[PDB]
Length: 457
Image (cartoon, rainbow, N blue to C red):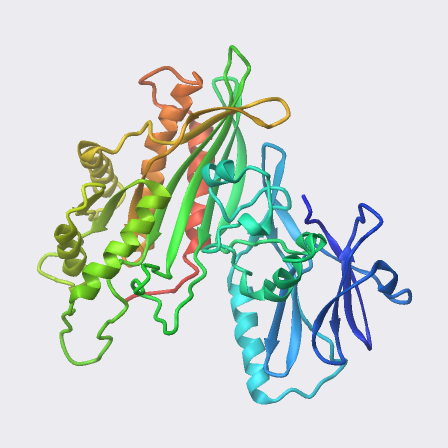
């Protein structure tokens, strides 16, 4: 990859960064200057001679906080996964570093850094130097050329805004690509297991969306351009050998979760009972949102959890009547009752949801599948996923994680059957240590991703 560990030296003239391993005779230095707070590109000969060299996993970017510019650094990482040679890292220790030995900063500036520190502490960020975690495996397959920041998915490139200065240089200087490492917000982990003497690698990744262009804003809902702002993809990955053949198969199965795509014009008042006005806007914005979702994922199966007995929500009924109004035959809507007691009667109901999705056209054979060679390059695309099940951000993360986990189990079985790791109509979950690894993997994910709010009432 172009990207890799970095070293820096800081002195009275500011901070100077370069790649820890310099390939070629041409290596770039990034300098954050104390003189004018500007970011500059320098020649190798201008890297400081004197000083403590500091090693860091990544320069995540810079931010201008009132008067001073600060470097945002991932100091250390831990490996949390490894898949087809690619290593996935979580950021462990970070720092926010200024050029000022001791500056007196005003209140407003100190408050900004507090708010950024709160976010860096509360979030879990992941990256891989050789694999682009902001894209699904199926999108990465379409990109091709392995990198770089230029083909990252901008919805999930969490440090997109922090890299603006570096991106502007990299447009006319491709050496700067080595400093631009896209990071995702949510979760990325793999586990090794064995199923019927086939070694396997199971992975799960959630990437959370970083919102959002436009002259005005609001988290909940969709803008006029069809973006929703709060949006996650959760992706289950598998790598396995075919027993006879010894061909290496790689699978991905993607799901989405996001705000109800109703226009962000919402009466967030105290008194009294609010009902939406869904003028031409809620039809228009929903249509535009679904046009993008269709281009990205194919057919969309929208799962809306009821969980009411005469307790009626404005945004609930609005979603359905809007979906019903557009009558798009590639958009399929389900309002599903998913109640307690939640360790028997709940999960029964999730298998019933899946039966109903199947009746609407969802197939458990609908997943990305490729064969790769002993060097890890693609030999064959056996299948591409052309649908997605979309759950709502507003339903309990507890319930939707259950829906997502169960659906991914149902698809996994077909993946296992397709590479002949299990017999047709067997149950992979009868393998106790494997189901344990699978269950921990998804419980960890829910832990990680719950980091949007602690609620509700």
